Image (tube, rainbow, N blue to C red; front, side, top):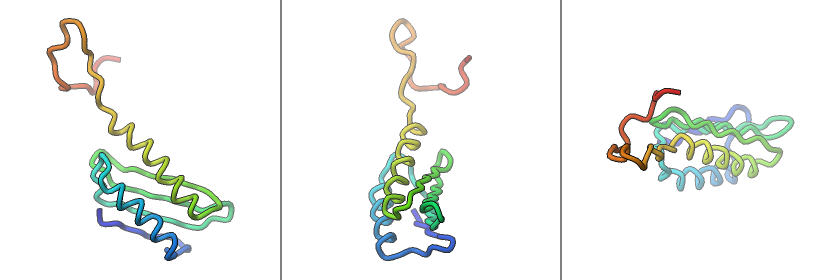
Length: 113
């Protein structure tokens, strides 16, 4: 977690910086790894543009949170990211029961359908 914050025209204010910082801090222990967390917080006419692009070992967790309230953008941002994170982490549901139980979580990608 290098914590990369690069905004467009709307620099990082003391209030906002502390906001995202606290969020990224706790989120640093999420079931991911967050290596290259690119947090881009810009100000748009019709709402704030919270573009948080995190580089996860599985891909990239892009947290998009648009809202007139800067603090609302930070919150809503971590919300969408969390949900998207849980999904990417979802990997617990093997065909149990029957005689096909004696098989650990081996190959679950590209089965049939």
